[PDB]
Amino acid sequence: HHHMEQKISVALKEIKRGANEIIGLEYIEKLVRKYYETNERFIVKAGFDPTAPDLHLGHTVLIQKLALLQQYGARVKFLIGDFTAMIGTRKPLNREQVLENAKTYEEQIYKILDQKHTEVCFNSTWLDALGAKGMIELCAKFSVARMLERDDFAKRHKENRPISIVEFLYPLLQGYDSVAMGADIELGGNDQKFNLLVGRFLQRAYGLNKEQSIITMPLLEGLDGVQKMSKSLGNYVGITEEPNAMFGKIMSVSDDLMWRYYTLLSAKTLEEIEDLKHGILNQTLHPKAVKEDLAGEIVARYYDNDQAFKAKE
Amino acid sequence: HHHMEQKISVALKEIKRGANEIIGLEYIEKLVRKYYETNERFIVKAGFDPTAPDLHLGHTVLIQKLALLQQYGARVKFLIGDFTAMIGTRKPLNREQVLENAKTYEEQIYKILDQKHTEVCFNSTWLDALGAKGMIELCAKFSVARMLERDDFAKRHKENRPISIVEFLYPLLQGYDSVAMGADIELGGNDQKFNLLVGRFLQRAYGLNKEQSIITMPLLEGLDGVQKMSKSLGNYVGITEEPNAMFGKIMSVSDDLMWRYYTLLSAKTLEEIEDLKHGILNQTLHPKAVKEDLAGEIVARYYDNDQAFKAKE
Image (tube, rainbow over all chains, first blue to last red; front, side, top):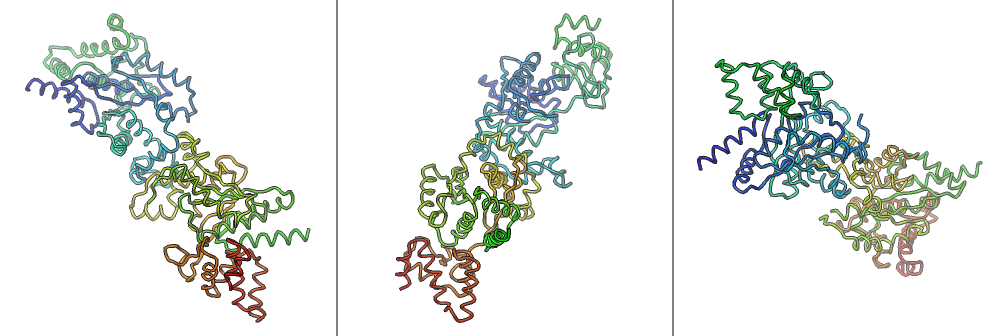
């Protein structure tokens, strides 16, 4: 079926776009074809900081990949990890704060995600029910040696530096979340690979018929282009910043950084971006109007089209 | 107070009698004096196999030290570890089996212990209530490096052999039992030192005003005198064996083994035993009558005096 093969080939390229690494692309391909064949959605898991929802564009990179995956049949489980947050620089949160912060996330994430195929989850739902016995059964499934292979543990173990045994529980609990949620894909940051792999190993160990694929996303470069975007470093673009200011901040970036932001932030397709790089070189497009198109797209995402024209002017 | 000092000095020698090692003898001394001064009892913890109560004399060695400690003010907490037994050669037990086995223990242990100052406990009582959050808080109190110093873990870690993370939980749970029970002394076998030390460390970490002393007891020699007593090795003396047979089994032992059994099994005092070794050498006592006195004492412990005379004849 030549037409479908083209559609699938394109879907796979968009899914890989901007990622650092994908484990399990074949399973992802099988789920995308099933979605096209049957309309059956598959489950995509991504975990978010219950404490800090003051967001800049760097925080949205993973959310943009989640929105892309919804185009190809993903049902998104936006997981707030309140269980560890309510236990405890890291003082413990109460339930009312957890709900307030989730509400805060929801003031924005549906400007990126398709709300109809998104579900906000709290892992305290199943983790409160785990019990001491559930914890025991979880810990029986994972070895000490594998655990000491996570990068920070190996260095601290080698350097004779303290590792608390509770630090062994957190990756197991994150992996268990994938078990309880039946995740088919889990997204995380590039430093999170080991932890994303735990859920994939634990799904097999708990007798599920499947193991989640995983995608790692890089950190977004700041407007400078050499430090990762950080409210600390003063190189961020706040999602709530006023349009004219947000538009001007994006104008600061170099031309090379513009394409990087295109890869990771823009709704334009790989093919459409390829045309932009062609016309700028064929002198059919000016790069300023391309940087303006990008700035306008980000302002229109968090506001609207009309307010995005005024920021340019 | 010269009289009391003599009483305390003797109490300490009887408490050390037969032990491999005592950690915290000063605290034990303070509790014994307080008992003599105020009649206030202190808490002695010892843990027992929920699954196997078919008992020989080797199983009673620790129980005899518990009975001795009751003479000096111990209130004994006979702890059945049903929490791990009901999770699971090691198939899981159900509640009815746990209660049946505890009943089986109670058909015998009060032939050794003072039932009035004994309490049978099940650690599922507080461990069911721990929750996943309690497990997390427990594991935050102990380091990975200290845990890998237990002898079997160090060898397996060095030999690149599998250690399951759940194996890190069991000593922490045993230590937590000491926290929940407020133990002042914990008894165990010589191989158990590391685990006994966990409770003593965890009591401090949970903010208790104290840390349990610990006593380790050796394994009893079999009737042969070179292998530890074992139902497997066929060198055991069953606590339920018929008197005449039980009496004759004890007669098998060598003279050197007789004194060892005196140290670990006999209600006679250190001073009284010293007199027995003197009269056998001064030829005022025959060693056969000494071995008979011991055999009779063990038969009378698990039966009665009258039935203990008939076994000799």
